[PDB]
Image (cartoon, rainbow over all chains, first blue to last red; front, side, top):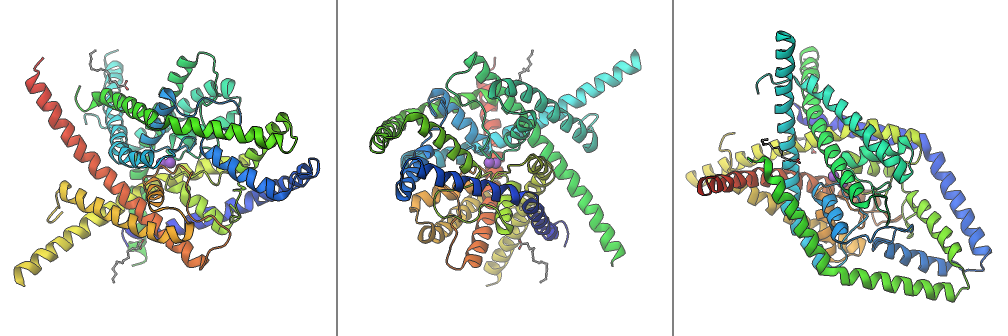
Length: 262
Length: 263
Ligand SMILES: [K+]
Ligand SMILES: [K+]
C-alpha cells in the first residue's frame, strides 16, 4: 500500500472530476455545437456555397493557423522577439501552442533543445525555491530581532505554504490589473489565464501579448516576461510545497487506516 | 554568483536559440504566409465573397474551434471519456489545449481542481522516480548476485541517467510504432509528438487519439493512456536526473572559473 497505492484514490478522483465537469456544462457544449451548425447552414445558404468547399477551406485554414495566422492582427508569430517568446514557452514547459515548428530540422532541433534546456529551467525554479526559502527565513529573523530590540529558522511548511499562496494570489491580482486594460479580458478570465500560464499547463485558449501593436511595446513585453517568470516560479514553488504537505497528510491518514482497520 | 547567476547563461541561451530558430526557417514561414494569402485571394475571387464576411466567419469559426470542433470527424471533445482525457491532460500539466472549459463555473472549478490535483500528480511522478530507483537498484543487486554465483547499491547518477534515456527512447519507439499505423503520422512526427507530450510541454499541434472512431476503441484508449503515463513519468525522471547532473557540472565549472580567474 504505502504512499504508492494512492493511485486508487487518484483514478477515482479523475473519475469524479470528469463526472462533475460533464454534468456542469454539457448543456453549454450542446448549445455551442447546435448554434454553430445552425449558422453553418445559414452561411452556406446566404452565399450559395457547398459543403465540400467549406470542408477543404476550413481544413486548410486550420493548417495555416497551425502555421500561426491568429485571425486578429497579431505579431509575426516568430521573430527575434517571436522566437524568444516561443523558446520561453518551451523551456518553462508551458506549451502554449501558439508557435510550433514546421520543418523536420526545426522539429529535431526542438527535440535536442527541450531535452537540454527544460530540465535546466525546472532546476532554476528549484534554485528560486531555495532562494525564496533562505531569504524569507532571513527576513523572519530580521522581524524577530526588530520586535525583540524595538536553514536557520527554517519556516514550517504550513507557514511557507500560506505566504506562498498569498504571494501567488497577490501577483495574480497585479498581473490581472495589468492585462485587463491591455488584452481586454475580464478579471476572472485574466485570473484563469494567470493560473493556466503559471501552473505550467498552458492551454493556449487564452494567451498573453500576441497583437502586432501595443502601447510601449518593449516595456510591455518586458513586463509580461518578468510577470510570467515570477508567477510560474511562485506557482511551481507552491505546487512542490503542498505536494510535500499532502504527502505528509496522506501518510498520516494511511497510518490511521492501518492502525484502526488492522 | 554561485549556482544563482546562471541566469546570465540562461538568457544568453534563449537568445542564441531564438536566433538559430529564426535563421533556420523564417523562409518556411514567409512561404506559408505568402501562399496562404494567395489562396485567400483565389478563394474570395472564385466565390465572389467579400473580406469582411471572411473576417467574421473565420473569427467566429475560431471561437467555435475554441469550443472544440476539430474540423475532421473527431470524438465528442468532452464526455465521460472526454472529460477523463481532459482531466488527465490537466493533472499531468501537459495542457494540450484541445479541451478547455467555457463556463465561469467550469473555470473556477478548474482553478480549484488544478490547485489541488496537479501537485498530487507531480508528487506521484516523484514517487514513480523513487520506485524506479529502488527497483533498479534491486535488479542490479540481483544481476551482481547472479554473475557471482552462476539506497542499497544506489546506482550513480550517470548510469541512472543513461538507462533512463534508454528507457525513454525505447518507449518512444514503441509509442511511435503504435501511433503511426493509427494516427497516420510519420515516424519523426510521432517521435516529436511523443517528446512534446512526455516533456509536459503539450503544444497541441499534434495530439493523441481524438477521432470519433478507432479500431478497438476501448483497448486503444487504454493503451494510449498507459503509454502517455509511462512516457511522461520516464521523461520527468530523466529531466530531474539530468537537472542534478548539470548542476553538478555547473558547480564544477564555476569552481574552475573562480580558481583560475581569481578576481
Ligand atoms: K507543463
Ligand atoms: K504544458
